[PDB]
Length: 362
Ligand SMILES: [Cl-]
Image 1 (cartoon, rainbow, N blue to C red):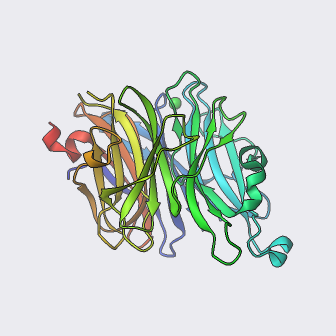
Image 2 (image 1 turned 180 degrees about the vertical axis):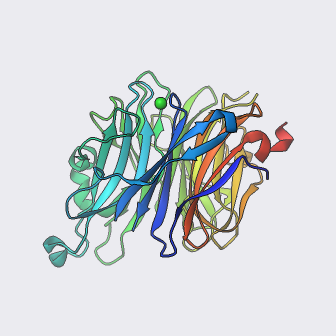
């Protein structure tokens, strides 16, 4: 398909950069591209230059605040709070080396849920805040580890403008069997002051992302997760992510077994009747992490409504993250996509419009 921009934003022959996260700032009309650097989190800011309809990426910088002493930082999970304008960067912190506790108990949970916030459009960040105890509580010792995202988080359009952070945890349900992962959501109605841990979806679900859409008559949260099956796993919640209805397989969205691959999903105003449509990116190969494709769902989150994918990039492609960026030069919705490519040797930024990706719609 034709695109507005394709630029490698992170590069490393040593596969130093992985796990992309993208965040669009609507007022500034800029993007924040995060990635893990093999471990800390790095960032590149880029302003959408209207006159040239290109994002001008600035110099890479380390998010020095997004780290705990003696820990490795991973899984950048950003969010823009529309009510306050504050930016949240959730992330995971794990000890850099085996701890004394782990020496005695191999599966002891030593993973930390953290966050740093910014009130100046991501130019500077607050000291890190460990949210582990407040968000997970007593369930903490029941897991071997867990993670959030990777990729952008969600803010609902409810009265409270609730924050929903997608996540997954490896549950130590059997002392002999290896811990099995299950996706879920963290939910806050007060801009991160308090957190609730939602119930798990089906077992063996891993990196997931959530979006909010209108279906039937009200708004629901759709969770789209990586699986070890041949198709993606999806589930919807009518209570902001605290409880999900029965998980379902989305056969139209392929997953390459046995490992599967992380994928991204976002909602955006319908170009036309449903209020929102969904856009999702993930490799399209039946058993390899290759050929990144963009898929559209005009009647979300109905599994049967997903479109055939449009090829965004041929060849090796892995994790990705999407962000809507307002209206494009051609008048249709503008999108930004950050994805791993070329055997993890780089992270590429792609910017395109709905008209470019899905011509038939126009
Ligand atoms: Cl902004």
